[PDB]
Image (cartoon, coloured by chain):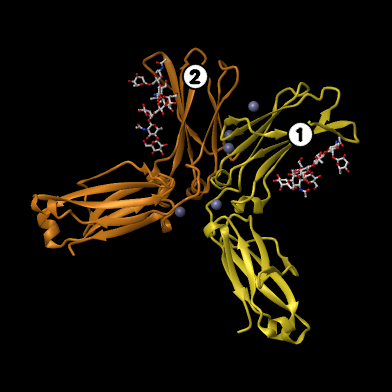
Chain colours: A orange, B yellow
Amino acid sequence: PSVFLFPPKPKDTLMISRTPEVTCVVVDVSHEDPEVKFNWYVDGVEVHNAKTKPREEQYNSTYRVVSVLTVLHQDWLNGKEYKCKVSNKALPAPIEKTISKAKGQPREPQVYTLPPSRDELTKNQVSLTCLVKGFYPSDIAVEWESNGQPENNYKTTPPVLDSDGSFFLYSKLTVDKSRWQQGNVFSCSVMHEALHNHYTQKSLSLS
Amino acid sequence: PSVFLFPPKPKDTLMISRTPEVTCVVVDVSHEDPEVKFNWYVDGVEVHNAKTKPREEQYNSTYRVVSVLTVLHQDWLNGKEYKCKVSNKALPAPIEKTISKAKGQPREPQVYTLPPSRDELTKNQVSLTCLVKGFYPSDIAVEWESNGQPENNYKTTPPVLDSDGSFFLYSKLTVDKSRWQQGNVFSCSVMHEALHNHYTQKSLSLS
Ligand SMILES: *[C@@H]1O[C@H](CO[C@H]2O[C@@H](C)[C@@H](O)[C@@H](O)[C@@H]2O)[C@@H](O[C@@H]2O[C@H](CO)[C@@H](O[C@@H]3O[C@H](CO[C@H]4O[C@H](CO)[C@@H](O)[C@H](O)[C@@H]4O[C@@H]4O[C@H](CO)[C@@H](O[C@@H]5O[C@H](CO)[C@H](O)[C@H](O)[C@H]5O)[C@H](O)[C@H]4NC(C)=O)[C@@H](O)[C@H](O[C@H]4O[C@H](CO)[C@@H](O)[C@H](O)[C@@H]4O)[C@@H]3O)[C@H](O)[C@H]2NC(C)=O)[C@H](O)[C@H]1NC(C)=O
Ligand SMILES: *[C@@H]1O[C@H](CO[C@H]2O[C@@H](C)[C@@H](O)[C@@H](O)[C@@H]2O)[C@@H](O[C@@H]2O[C@H](CO)[C@@H](O[C@@H]3O[C@H](CO[C@H]4O[C@H](CO)[C@@H](O)[C@H](O)[C@@H]4O[C@@H]4O[C@H](CO)[C@@H](O[C@@H]5O[C@H](CO)[C@H](O)[C@H](O)[C@H]5O)[C@H](O)[C@H]4NC(C)=O)[C@@H](O)[C@H](O[C@H]4O[C@H](CO)[C@@H](O)[C@H](O)[C@@H]4O)[C@@H]3O)[C@H](O)[C@H]2NC(C)=O)[C@H](O)[C@H]1NC(C)=O
Ligand SMILES: [Zn+2]
Ligand SMILES: [Zn+2]
Ligand SMILES: [Zn+2]
Ligand SMILES: [Zn+2]
Ligand SMILES: [Zn+2]
C-alpha cells in the first residue's frame, strides 16, 4: 500500500473563480483486506469536507482509492499545509503525506514582449516572443490572445532557474508575417501568484 | 517530559548581520532516567549542526535540557520548517515539535509620520506619531532616531489585526516641545520582512 498526494492544477489556484483541490491516492490496496480510512488535516487541524470515491479494482488484483479535498484559494496561496492520512489494517502504522504550495518568498514576474528578429522578417511566418523573468515560485501559466480571441499557435519553455534564484521562461507565438505587417495587436497573458490579482498582460504590435 | 520549541528573535531574522536560532527545550526530564537525544530536521531532512547544552537540574527534582539550532537568514524567510525530535527512554514514543516563520502572503508596510496635534502644542512635551499599516505577517521592529543617535523615549503598540487581514500599529515618541519647535529631524525606523532589505525609515520635522 502506497500513498500519493497531488496538488491542484496551477491555473486553478490563480483564478478565484475556479475550485482548486488536493487529491490523495492510495494504490496496492490488497483486495483481501481493502478497508481504507482517510483523515485530512489543514495545518494539523482535522477537517471533514473531503469527498472520497468508491474503490476501483485494478487489473493487477489490487484496489485503488481516491479522496479529494477542496482547498480555498486564499488558504493555498497563504501556505496552509494539507495532510492526508491513510489507515488500513494491513499496515503496521498509518501512512501520512503532506503537501503545500511551493514555499519561498514570492517574486513578481517582469513580462517583456520581443518582436521578430529582422532576419526572420523574410520568412512566411514570424516568431513573437514573450520573456517572463524574475518570478518565484515557478508555478505559472502563459497564453496568447489577439482581438478578443485566443492565439493558440504557441509553445512555451519550462521555467528555468536563473542565477539569482528566480525563474524565467520564454513563450513563442508563431504568426503569418502578413498578420504582423498588417499591424494586429498580440497579447502575452501571464498568471502568477505574485502579480496583482495574479494576472498581467503585455501587448506586441508592429512599431 | 514536555518539549517547547521557540523561534528566533524577530530582529535577528531581519538583519543579515545577525544569527537567528531556534531553541528546543525539554523539561520534566526525570533525573532517574535523564538520557535525552535530540534530532533536528529542516523540511524533513535531518541536520547535524545543532549545539546541545549539558542538562541542568531544576529545584523541583527534574532535569531541563536545551538544544539550539542556528538557522540561515534566507531559510527562515523562505518558510523552511524546523522540527525538533526529543527521545527519552521514559516516553512511549519520541516527542516532535515543528516551527516555521509565520505563514501567509507577505504584505509591505506603509509608514506614515504624524506631527503633534495642534492642541498638544501647548504642553511641555509633544507626541510624534508613526503609523505603520498594511503589513503581514505581524513580526516587526520599530525604533526612533535623530541626528545619528537613538531617540529612546518611545512606546509602540502591539500589532492590531485590521479589517483587511493585514496588521497596523502606532509608535509614539515623546519629545520636549522646544526640540520640535527648534526643527530637529526625527526618524521612524521600521524593520519588516516585506520591505526592501527588510528596512525603511520615514522622517518627521516641523513643517
Ligand atoms: C497496480 O495497478 C495500479 C493502477 O495503475 C495502473 O497503471 C496503468 C499504467 C495501467 O496501464 C495498469 O498498469 C494499472 O492498472 C498501480 O498504481 C500506480 O502505482 C504507481 C506507483 O507504484 C504510481 O506511480 C506514481 O505516479 C505519480 C504520478 O501519477 C500521476 O501521473 C500518472 C501518469 O504519469 C497517472 O497514472 C496518475 O493517475 C497521476 O495522474 C495525475 O493524477 C492527479 C490526481 O488526480 C492529477 O491531479 C489532479 O488533476 C485534476 C485534473 O486531472 C485537477 O487538476 C485536480 O485539481 C488535481 O489534483 C494530475 O492531473 C494527473 N496527471 C496526469 C499527467 O495524469 C508519480 O508522481 C509517482 O512518483 C514519485 O514516484 C516514485 C516514488 O514512489 C519516484 O520515481 C519519485 O520519488 C517520484 O517523486 C509515482 O511514480 C501510479 O500513479 C499509480 N497509478 C494510478 C492510476 O494511481 C500499481 O502500482 C500497480 N501495482 C503493482 C504491484 O503493479
Ligand atoms: C520544574 O521546573 C522547570 C524549570 O522551570 C522553573 O520555573 C521557574 C519559574 C522557577 O522559578 C522554578 O519554578 C523552576 O525551576 C519547569 O519548566 C517550565 O515548564 C513550563 C511548562 O510546565 C514551561 O512553560 C512554558 O513556557 C513557555 C514560555 O517560556 C518562555 O518564557 C518563560 C517566561 O514566560 C521562561 O521561563 C522560558 O525560559 C521561556 O523564555 C524564552 O525562552 C526562549 C528560549 O531560550 C527565548 O528565545 C530565545 O531567546 C534568545 C535570547 O533570549 C534568542 O533571541 C534566541 O534566538 C531565541 O530562540 C525567549 O527569548 C525567552 N523569552 C522570555 C520572555 O524569557 C510558554 O510558551 C509555554 O506555553 C504554551 O503553554 C501551555 C501549553 O503547554 C499553554 O498555556 C499554551 O498552549 C501555550 O501555547 C509554557 O507555558 C516553562 O517554560 C518551563 N521553564 C523553563 C525555564 O524551561 C517545570 O514545569 C517544572 N516541573 C514541575 C512538575 O513543576
Ligand atoms: Zn470526518
Ligand atoms: Zn509542516
Ligand atoms: Zn487571489
Ligand atoms: Zn547528528
Ligand atoms: Zn534578507
Work out which residue is located at the far front of the displayed protein and give it: B148
Secondary element at tag 2: loop
Residue A1 in sight:
yes
Residue A47 in sight:
no
Who's the residue at 78% across and 83% down the image?
B124
In the figure, B142 relative to A170: above or below?
A: below
Q: Where the C terminus of chain B falls, by quadrant?
A: bottom right
Residue that badge 1 annotates? B53
Left or right: where A15 falls relative to B7: left
Closer to viewer: mark 2 or mark 1: 1
Who's the residue at 39% across and 41% down the image?
A9
Residue type at mark 1: give it. Answer: Lys
Who's the residue at 71% across and 71% down the image?
B172
Label annotation for residue A1:
2
Secondary element at tag 1: loop
Residue type at mark 2: give it. Answer: Pro
Q: Quadrant of residue B150?
A: bottom right
Q: Which quarter of the rendered image does ligand 2 occupy?
A: top right
Who's the residue at 36% across and 51% down the image?
A133
Of the pair A163 and A81, the residue shown nearer to us: A163
In the figure, A98 relative to A30: above or below?
A: below
Q: Does the closest atom of ligand 1 sit within 8 Å of the Cβ of label 2?
A: no
